[PDB]
Image (cartoon, coloured by chain):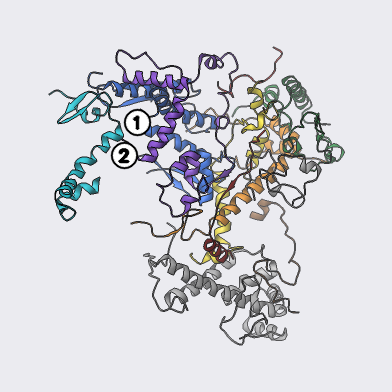
Chain colours: A yellow, B brown, C orange, E red, F blue, G purple, H green, I cyan
Amino acid sequence: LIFGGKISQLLSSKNLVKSLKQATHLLPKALSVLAKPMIFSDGYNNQNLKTATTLLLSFIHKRYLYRKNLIVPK
Amino acid sequence: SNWWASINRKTGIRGPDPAPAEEHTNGPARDII
Amino acid sequence: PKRRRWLLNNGSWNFWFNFDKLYSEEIVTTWILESLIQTYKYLHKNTELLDFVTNKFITLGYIAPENANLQSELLSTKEIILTNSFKRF
Amino acid sequence: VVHLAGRCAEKLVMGEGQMTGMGSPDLFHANLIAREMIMSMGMGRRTGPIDLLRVAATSDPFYYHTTDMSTEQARVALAEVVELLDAAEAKAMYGLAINWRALQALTQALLDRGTITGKEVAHILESNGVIHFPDPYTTGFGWDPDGSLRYPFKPDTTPDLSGARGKTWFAGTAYDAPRNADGTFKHGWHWNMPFSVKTE
Amino acid sequence: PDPYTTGFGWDPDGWHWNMPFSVKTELPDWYKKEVERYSY
Amino acid sequence: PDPIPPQLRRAVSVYEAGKALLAYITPDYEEIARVSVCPLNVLTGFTLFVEDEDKNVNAILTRSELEGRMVVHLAGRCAEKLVMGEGQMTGMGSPDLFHANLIAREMIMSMGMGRRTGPIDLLRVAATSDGDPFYYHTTDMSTEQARVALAEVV
Amino acid sequence: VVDLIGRNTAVEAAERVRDALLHPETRERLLAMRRWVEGGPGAPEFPPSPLSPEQTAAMSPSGPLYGNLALNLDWWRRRQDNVISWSAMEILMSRRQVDLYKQDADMTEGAIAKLGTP
Amino acid sequence: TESYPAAVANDIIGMGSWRLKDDVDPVIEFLVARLEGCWREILDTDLCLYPREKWKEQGWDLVDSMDPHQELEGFSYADIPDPAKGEAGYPRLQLENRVYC
Amino acid sequence: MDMHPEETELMGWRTNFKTNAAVVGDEPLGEFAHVAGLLVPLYAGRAAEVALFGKDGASLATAQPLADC
């Protein structure tokens, strides 16, 4: 639910490397994958990241699902 | 019948009953509220 | 006021009790990656629906980022459009 | 033992992965008892009679206890706390395992009645053939290094690289992503995802 | 050259980037023993 | 350069000139207001920018915009190297180097722009209620995560 | 300032100066920019082009080729290693720099487990 | 709040969320954008997606020559590098389909 | 003697001058050498006692500059 919008933004973005680069590891199939695609927006919101990291850290620091001995220095 | 004495903390702790039940979601929001 | 909890310097940098860090990070990144992969795999098969909903959402209106100032519930017509698009068969 | 009993019971019944976070206060209470036995009451075999805890609550991460001892002594004391917690958990799992039928009957009775009294608890446990602890001590209980329980009457006092999945990127190479048993990438990863996985 | 501002579209009028990575992490035996002790 | 030594004037001139040139040729950057190299025989040098209230303010920070800002920040020391040499560079570029490093760390650890660290919130900004008008909430990372993020930042 | 900076730093600098002296174009550019820094009547105006000749500067104005400066910073990533080390000196410095240095590091026995393995 | 007509809406969309929108020619991309925009604009309120059990459940929405059995869950277009010359699989054929009613 | 107030800061990149008993030729002092030249006057108090008397001649009179070195 948090990351659906960024996933659709990634799926609906034009890769500009194949529109920018012109004519060892040639052709715009291996030439375009040498580096990160030129997605216009990129990044994340820093609020979605805050919610996701808070949820996962609250899962692992408050449940002790697998490692219970980590409650020793609490 | 002595289903203990094989309880391993390294390979996973399991009882004799093969899992309690399934989990019913009916949506994240309906789980929430 | 110097630090006195030096534990490991050869092989990695670790102070006395940081044992709950590798497990924590390798659960956080794994779970976030799995959820993003699940979202990508769902939205990979609904790209036509995404384009249709986007086309029907432009004509209804949106807040342009012109910074003339100083979206968690969705309006009613924009909900009718999305429910119609998700009819399937 | 009693404070670790609830989370041990829910781990045995519901499974290891379906345990909820309601056992955290009781787990911290058992850890607190072990910590006060080792570092405060001087009941440690290796730690011995020395006062190590100096309560500095005085009321950022909220520390209550606070200790100034050295790292080696802290390692020894926390190892003793861990071994006491392991002994208590082993005894709790031993009791819940030998009284599995009584535990299941008490669970069903609690589900049916919501609340229950002491006499009904005693009647259910005695009618289901309960086994009592001869001792209240966790002495001799623990976990073996291989992973098996202690005092369980044993002592006494390549990934698939077929066709389309192999014709992908580097495949058999140290530069490949981790793969599952069926050849699919770990976490269902693919090469167009915006994140890079870590090699196993 | 500013991208995202002009061009890229008709009008009638080797090495990948998602390379998996690793960290060395040459831990000693006592640290592995402590990790195994607290990993339960 | 009546008081100011010739090599000092040349150094500050090269620095401010490179910074102003890269700010001019960087798209969607702030307009240069004034480039001063020892204005009233005072040992300082600066390249000012107009503080517009339109456009960005705080709506969305594009990674191309952040990379352009970081390049403009590194431009002064790059010009000093490329003109005077490696050994004639001095420490006048330290605030710009700090700002470029802050932009890089913000992109890696706050916006999830790195492919290896991933979308993890390890750094947050905060406003102080004098010194700097802001500080940073930091998450205590392990050595492996810190090394991966450092590799991306470098 | 050799005693002030350290013999290892002086040796690394000597290696860099040797590598620059072996290339005549780099050597002449360095001499010309040293002349401009020193100034005087012998200064030949601004130093020459910064290793980008007129054929590589005319290779990309707003006319021919172009567009490589439009790519994001990751496309300018000239160093990429898939195995990130456990120590920051390996990430920061090059292999020769780590081999020459790292006896100045404040470490116990990591300073034998770090590049140029004997 | 500002809205746009359907013509410039589909021009803003362009090709859209096509899986192979980056490897196609600009002429093909312009034509696909124009025809899909004409569909989504003229045939609005009655344009349905074709039943998935006819074309999409069989994996014909995106087929790749090197992955005919859909062993990569439709991610072969970026999971598999393009074949070398002469090497089996060359030339690789990729077909993306969009069926509406 | 009309002089810049920040003449101490200007003393690094100035060439072919002389102050007190120290001359600077055509090679200017960098910031590193200029600030690292301050360590010698602070060490000279201890160096005089060590050179003229020995280790036991070191006193508390020359102990404060060593802590700022």
Q: Viewer-proximal residue, B17 or F44? A: F44
Q: Position of residue H11 (x, y in %)?
A: 69, 23
Residue H61 shows in this picture: no
Q: Which residue reaches farthest right?
A: H54
The image's mark for residue A39 is none
Q: Viewer-proximal residue, F57 or C83? A: F57
Q: Position of residue C5 (x, y in %)?
A: 42, 60
- Label 2 marks which chain's residue? G
Q: Pointers 1 and 2 in contact (CB under 8 A)?
A: no
Q: Give the class, few, some or many, for how many residues have Cα within 10 Å of label 1's Cα (few <14, many ≥20).
A: some
Write down the residue under mark 2. Answer: G3
- Label 1 marks which chain's residue? F
Is residue F65 shown left or right of residue C52?
left
Residue G117 shows in this picture: yes
Three-letter amino acid code at disc 1? Thr
Three-letter amino acid code at disc 2? Asp
Q: Give the class, few, some or many, for how many residues have Cα within 10 Å of label 2's Cα (few <14, many ≥20).
A: few
Residue for point 74% across, 19% down? H27
Disc 1/disc 2 C-alpha distance (Å): 20 Å
Residue for point 39% across, 20% down? G31
- SS for dot 2: helix
Q: Viewer-proximal residue, H66 or H11? A: H66
Residue for point 14% across, 30% down? I20
The image's mark for residue F90 is 1
Is residue G25 shown left or right of residue I47?
right
